[PDB]
Length: 59
Length: 61
Image (cartoon, rainbow over all chains, first blue to last red; front, top):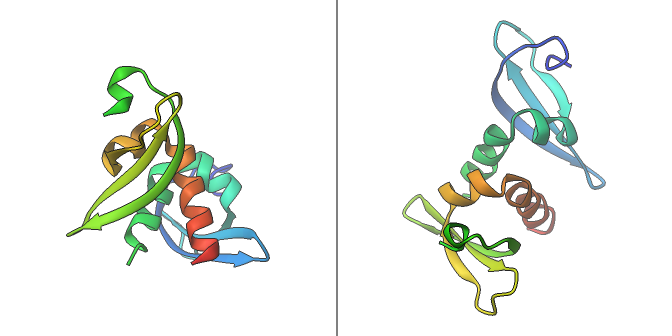
C-alpha cells in the first residue's frame, strides 16, 4: 500500500509464510517503518527485487 | 539458450549455484532434453515462472 501511495521499495527485509500465504516485510524509501506486503502484490510490483531476495537467500 | 530459438519454457527442473553463479535447468516445450540457462537470462524472460519455482522450492525446503 506504499505501492498504492506510489512509494519506492528499497529492500525486502524478510518473508513470512503463514499456512501457504506469503507476506514480505518491505522497506520503502522515505518511510521509517517497514510495511507488510502480500507476495501477490510484491511479485507484480517489484519482481526483480523478489527474485534477488530469493536468489540471495539461496544460501 | 532455448530462449534465442523462440522456444517456450515449460518448467524449471532445478537450480545450481557455482561460486555465486546460478544456473537453471529448464524444460522447454516440445524439446525432450532440458537445457541449462543462466539465471540472468531466466530472470528476464520468465520472471513469473522463476518466482513460482522459488516459492515452491522454499515451501518444501
